[PDB]
Amino acid sequence: PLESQYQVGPLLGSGGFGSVYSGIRVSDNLPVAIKHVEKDRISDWGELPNGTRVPMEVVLLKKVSSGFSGVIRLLDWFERPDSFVLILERPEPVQDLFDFITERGALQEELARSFFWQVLEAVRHCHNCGVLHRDIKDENILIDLNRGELKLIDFGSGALLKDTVYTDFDGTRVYSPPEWIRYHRYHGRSAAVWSLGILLYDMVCGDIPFEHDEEIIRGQVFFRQRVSSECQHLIRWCLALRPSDRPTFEEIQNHPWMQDVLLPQETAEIHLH
Ligand SMILES: N[C@H]1CCCN(c2ccncc2Nc2ncc3ccc(-c4c(F)cccc4F)nn23)C1
């Protein structure tokens, strides 16, 4: 079933998330990504309408599946004796935002605006669908280089969105908020906004603002690169120490820095082609 349907290519990456390979669907040559996750390494388990036990990642991906292109599409999944295999869409050509920033260094603000806006729209979509990603970062954002469209990947640390406190966390520590570091407690939306602040800083400075717990806890943001006052203000707002002092998604998108965003295709023409 699986081995007949797909031609496996090189390894794209491995780590805490598992192992992910490039591949091709034999029937129609469709580019895909093939993600393997060992059962023992899965703590978060969900359940389909069937009653079938699957990784929460599959549940979340199904919940966010639609025409909306800002989230990676799950094409299929398979259970093996000791692992699960996910077949995902693969844009081509594509580059993840981490590599993109490594190559380019600090992004021009017009480009960071387009990218950040698309990330916000994607994250809003997830939340509307009842899904919290919990690992928003440059490494988990794909750039469709022809269309100038960004997509969220790796819902392996995510969870169902709830209004009560989370006391578990398996995402990336340097993107995690001060309330997690200090109290091992956070709420979904305000934690997401913190991680978005980290992301935005990363885009416009070419590196993350905090390395150590004490930096995160203190929350003093220093700019190493030239960044506009409007952008600095939004970043500092997202990175408010008190969760309730952070902006809502609406307030982020209504912020002066976020106005007159380019269309994805405009973005590709100007910055990517
Ligand atoms: N920073 C990326 C490196 C590649 C693997 N990666 C992932 C980690 C956890 N889950 C999934 C992924 N990757 C993933 N899921 C679907 C896709 C689709 C495309 C890609 C991809 C990519 F992320 C980089 C370069 C080429 C690619 F095809 N990765 N990808 C993080």
Image (spheres, rainbow, N blue to C red):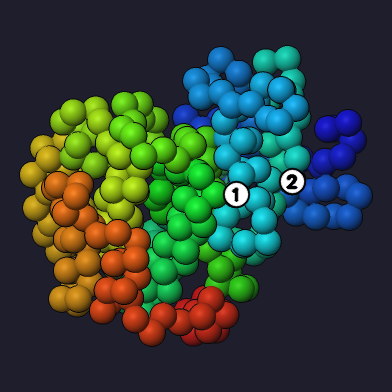
Query: Does the CB distance between marks 2 and 1 fall below 8 Å?
Result: no
Numbered mark located on residue 64 in the image: 1
Q: Nearer the viewer, residue 201 or 261?
A: 261
In which quarter of the view is residue 57 placed?
A: top right
- Residue at the image point whose x is 51% and y is 45% from the top: 130
Q: Which element carries disc 1, helix, strand or loop?
A: loop
Numbered mark located on residue 75 in the image: 2
Q: Can residue 108 be seen by looking at this rendering?
A: no
Query: For the image shown, how many numbered marks are present on the structure?
Result: 2
Which residue type does callout 2 highlight? Leu
Left or right of 222 on screen, residue 184? right
Task: Relative to 245, say whether 62 is above or below.
Answer: above
- Residue at the image point whose x is 75% and y is 40% from the top: 76
Place of residue 79 in the rendered image (x, y in percent of width and height, measured from the top left) = 74, 24
Which residue type does callout 1 highlight? Val
- Quadrant occupied by the N terminus: top right
Whether label 2 lies within 8 Å of ligand 1 gets the answer no
Of circles 2 and 1, the one toward us is 1
Q: Residues within 10 Å of mark 2 (few under 14, many from 20)?
A: some
Task: Relative to 235, say whether 183 is above or below.
Answer: above
Place of residue 7 in the rendered image (x, y in percent of width and height, measured from the top left) = 82, 42
